[PDB]
Image (cartoon, grey):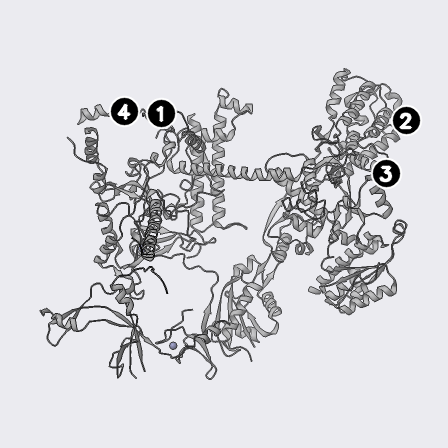
Amino acid sequence: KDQDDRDHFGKKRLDLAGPLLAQLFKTLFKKLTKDIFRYMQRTVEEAHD
Amino acid sequence: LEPGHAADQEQAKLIRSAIEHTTLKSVTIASEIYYDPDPRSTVIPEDEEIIQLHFSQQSPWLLRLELDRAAMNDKDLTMGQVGERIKQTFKNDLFVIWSEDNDEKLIIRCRVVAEEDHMLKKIENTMLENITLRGVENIERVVMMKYDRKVPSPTGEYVKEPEWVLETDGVNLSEVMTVPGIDPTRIYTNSFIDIMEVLGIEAGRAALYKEVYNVIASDGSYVNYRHMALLVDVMTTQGGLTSVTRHGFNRSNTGALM
Amino acid sequence: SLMSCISVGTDPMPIITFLSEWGMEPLEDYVPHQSPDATRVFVNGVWHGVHRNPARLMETLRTLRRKGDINPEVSMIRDIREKELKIFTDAGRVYRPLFIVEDDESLGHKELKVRKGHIAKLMATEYQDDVEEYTWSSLLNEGLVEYIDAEEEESILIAMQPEDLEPAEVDPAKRIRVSHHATTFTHCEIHPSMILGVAASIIPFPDHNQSPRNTYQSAMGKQAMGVFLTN
Amino acid sequence: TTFRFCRDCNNMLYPREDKENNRLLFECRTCSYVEEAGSPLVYRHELITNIGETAGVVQDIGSDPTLPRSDRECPKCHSRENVFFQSQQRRKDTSMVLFFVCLSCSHIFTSDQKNK
Amino acid sequence: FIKRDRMRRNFLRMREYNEFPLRAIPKEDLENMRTHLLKFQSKKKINPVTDFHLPVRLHRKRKTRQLKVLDENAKKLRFEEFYPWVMEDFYNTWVGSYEAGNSDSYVLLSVEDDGSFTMIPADKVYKFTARNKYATXXXXXXXXXXXX
Amino acid sequence: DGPTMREITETIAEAKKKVLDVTKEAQANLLTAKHGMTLRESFEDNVVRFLNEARDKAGRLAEVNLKDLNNVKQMVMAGSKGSFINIAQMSACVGQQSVEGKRIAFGFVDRTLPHFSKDDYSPESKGFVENSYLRGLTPQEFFFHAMGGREGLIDTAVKTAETGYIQRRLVKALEDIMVHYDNTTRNSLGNVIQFIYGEDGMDAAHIEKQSLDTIGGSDAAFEKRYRVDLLNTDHTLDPSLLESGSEILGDLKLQVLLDEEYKQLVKDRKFLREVFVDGEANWPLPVNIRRIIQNAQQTFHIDHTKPSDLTIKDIVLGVKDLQENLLVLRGKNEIIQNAQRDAVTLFCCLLRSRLATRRVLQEYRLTKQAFDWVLSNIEAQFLRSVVHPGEM
Amino acid sequence: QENERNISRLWRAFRTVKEMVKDRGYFITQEEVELPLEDFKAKYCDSMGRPQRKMMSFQANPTEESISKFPDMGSLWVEFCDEPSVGVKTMKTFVIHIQEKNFQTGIFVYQNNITPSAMKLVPSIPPATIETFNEAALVVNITHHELVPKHIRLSSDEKRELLKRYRLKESQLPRIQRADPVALYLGLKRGEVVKIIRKSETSGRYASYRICM
Ligand SMILES: [Zn+2]
Ligand SMILES: [Zn+2]
């Protein structure tokens, strides 16, 4: 068998707004959850409302 | 080639057969290993003929191989001179037998004074790769070319006289120069570096000029002799060959600013 | 190109669930000595198992793929020499619509699936807009046009002009074309002029013009003066 | 070259020289399973490889639409309906000798007129 | 040779057998015992448990306020039972492992004395492997022997 | 025309039959490749050679069919715009579209496009465009032509991007090099690159391609031209050439001078045989003698059948006195005069070749004022062809 | 077989040695260099057929013109070696022999290689020098090639005259490396200016001046 061709257009995937906003909204959502939990730990640790 | 042996194909075939690298693997169709404990007698019914002839304490393991007759033709070889080469390679530790050219099947067998198989397999690598049957190193695919050569006639004007000239793939200038059967006073290399090393600085200069001039004439353009001469000279005025780089004139004094 | 689109991705679970109902042996039960001629099944590169009858299974998946059950964006390839059957339903693939050619017809030779009646109903709905609700989706669900990416394009034979390469058999001003020795035409090109992009589509008679001039004009077409909108 | 495996151990059988009876044997170094030798051959390298040119021949090769069609008859069944394709062994020095595959008896007859 | 743009007017102007019953065993026996499957990996065809001899034994071998990650149920119950069982005598060894994928749909048709059959749903399935046939090993001796 | 279109169709058709025959002989394994290449390389060279031969022949037929009333023929014959390849691709056939110097490779499984069969080695499917730009192109040909166009653009872009870097390395490589007021090329630090600029001391704005009459011609022509005998009848002097030809014959001194000139020309011929071993006589040199001779003949009204008033000592001693007037170096030491003679040897050989007694008395028929004017023009133009010191 | 070929290579190499010594300025006649192969085999080969390189060692005497131009130029002693690997003791015999015979220069030709201790024991007797050349390297004379112009070793007075007429320092001349097979062919030293006469295609005869490193 010949060496696997990488220039075959079928083996290539395009990215529109869907995948890009999926990565972006994914990371931003993770940061949001982490920050919310940080506020929770600060609240229960500092003993406040 | 030499002017005396010009326009000759057989002589150029001898020169090609004297410099073109050849190896034992080139001629080898296949090889196979056999267990044959008795040194003289062979279980194989065919090779018995060889056993009958080439005979008239040693390893029980047999190494055997077969050669392409076409390879024995295209690259002129003799089963005899091959066996000579191996015998003078490993000397006496490896006993050797080889079939005749008359045999429709070319056969070669060898033995030695843990398991013997691994030892044989090592020797197989040495046989295929490390044996060169003929020719000097780094020479391949010698092409015969009929090149017309302008030479003066005794009638006062030049005449084109075709002669066989050997084009060569790969390079090894020093070894090729010493071989008898060619002009040692004529030879060229597309790599001007080798010309510099072997034939010295002046030859390196002229060769460099030829290399530059070649690309110019290939482009289909004309450039005056003055400019190319100046360029070539600059690259050679400190001895040897000097690169045109930022490591080729910024590593020698010219003023810190320059 | 003018008819090229990008896939969006579907769900491979219903397909994997549907394969095991027809005897698709799982991978962990595979023995190469008991079933050497089994065809491996691949779903998005994941090897789920093999099957000892890829013909009827492939025909079933194709018939159910043309009826509109499976999303047409999914591209399935069946490599014979490699003895594989790749299934791609991931987002990012670029496909293009092409017609479907059938060999079994009442005329005795091969012919397209779409006929003149479907064209008559289609144009009736187009010029009517009484209506018959016959659009592109109705042409797709009846198995008359199919999307093909660059992976499935490896295992299909496409014809350029319909009425020039499908039927079986000259003025010197026309161009010389190929022959129709090939019989196994599976698909047919809608129109070759669709291979060009938007900028090259403005070029008049680009066949009679050299390519770099088509490129230069395609570059100058992105900066000419005009009217972009009315507002 | 076409070696056997051990019983229970299923490991490869390394060759063992029998110095007592002076004969080849096949052993398993994990256990004490040693069987006799039915052949003195052990290793064959075979440098110039000619196999693999006709690789990937399947029973369903006649239903491939991408493959061409020819009108040459088979030397066996004399069927002019066949499918031809070149060698499957991909290499620089691979010849372009066609391989005829009849669509009746599934015989593979080539088109080489020099060597058959 | 010209673009036909008057298609609106053209379209406007043109348009022997043996029957045996099946039964479901009462769920009391299913609540008492769980049915698992056995599959050997020694290639030998026979290998019955009678030839496995006796006695056959199959047995299983300060910080402030912080953060936890999470986990679910069935996966946790299968993760806590990470001790595989073994069957031996007092010598042959068989050590089994989970199969997981071969759960799905597996119904047992146990044949009794009569022609009827008793169907039992399979809980799990395990692959038993004959262990310690040759009897050898080394650890650090093999780590130093592999450095040659 | 019609018949020309049919001749092009048959020309391409014969090449198609040749590619089909070589294709069948290659599929039958009946063709052995030559040394250095394999079967596929020789086959592709044969197919490409036949296709380019048919395209060139069709282009020749399309070029011959056109008349002189066509404007493209007037533009091609004018040398402004247009060429033979343009009308060969527009009127006859485009040709073979090659990528990276090779045929259209298989972008798919054993085929170039998914519109052909597998293992197809026909020239049409491998990239041959048998249609012309007058009748349009097919899609499978327009695609390959687009590949060739994009490849041309990319290649030109890379050649320019590297050409700039090469240009900067050459400019910054050769910068502080000039010629001082001593006719010696040396840089700013005093390192001597060339003792004489261009190894001759001549600017590149006054050099013209000249022909060497010393090596040109056969031995019988050499002895027939450069031998003017006075006491022998082999190469005697025609007395009707000059006015005093009846008194020149029988002179021993002028015959000795002719012997010295002839021996000098023979030594110059051996020297040119050792310098130029290729046999070419055309080399760039300063001072155009032919224009000076023609200006002298058209200035002094020198026509044929006119006896000249020159003698042998006037031409011989005139050339010998002109050879000392050629000066490039203004020194007087040993090495300076050695470099001057070694830098003027070739030009002196050219002047001794073009300024022979037979060539002036027989062909040119120059007089006294015409010959002296030619000498003054040669010395003058030689003094103007000197490179100026201080030029970069 | 191999013996006759080795005799031929040793004969061409010996002819190259005579040509090299003759180019240095020593008195060797033309008929002495143009000696055929059959005479060389009839002189320096035993009855068995093997050549004797110990008998091929000879002495070179400078010409009258070389003494007139270079008054400090002395005689030369040329020796070979029958050993494949030249030991240190043979080199000691060569150096001590040169010191006894009182030669200004010396040339020693080896077959394969020499021990590093011998190469270190070369600059031991100033101002005398020893030139170590290989038998396989002197098979072909490099000066008979077309791409190699003519080289002439100048003197001290001509060097000072050149630098005085051209107004140059020794560093301003084009430098040539000692490792040049041409510099080793002529046996050049530090501070020696050589003249290169080359046949240009724009002037016929171009001259150059180089100086060793
Ligand atoms: Zn075992
Ligand atoms: Zn058949």
User: Residue at the location (30% across, 49% down)?
Assistant: C89
Classify residue E75 as left or right of residue F150. left
Which of pointers 4 and 1 indicates the residue nearer the eye? Answer: 1
Q: Bin the neighbour count of mark 4 within 10 Å (Cα to Cα): few under 14, some 14-19, many 20 and up.
A: few
The image position of residue F70, as x and y in percent, is 48, 21
Circle 1 residue: C227
Which of pointers 1 and 2 indicates the residue nearer the eye? Answer: 1
Callout 3: helix, strand or loop?
Answer: helix
**In the image, is the residue at mark 3 within 8 Å of ligand 2 by its beta carbon?**
no
Which of pointers 2 and 4 indicates the residue nearer the eye? Answer: 4
Q: State whether discs 4 and 3 lie on one chain.
A: no
Classify residue E75 as left or right of residue B258. left
The image position of residue C129, as x and y in percent, is 20, 29
CA distance for labels 2 and 3: 38 Å
Type of residue at label 1?
Val
Q: Bin the neighbour count of mark 3 within 10 Å (Cα to Cα): few under 14, some 14-19, many 20 and up.
A: few
Q: Which quadrant: the N terminus of chain F?
A: top left
Residue F238, compared with residue B41, is above or below; it is above
Which label was assigned to residue E5?
Answer: 4
Residue G72, compared with residue C197, is above or below; it is below
Ligand 1 is in which quadrant of the figure?
bottom left
- Which of the pair E87/B118 is nearer the observer? E87
Circle 3 residue: F334
Type of residue at label 4?
Asp
Q: State whether discs 4 and 1 lie on one chain.
A: no
CA distance for labels 1 and 2: 100 Å
CA distance for labels 4 and 3: 96 Å
Which of pointers 2 and 3 indicates the residue nearer the eye? Answer: 3
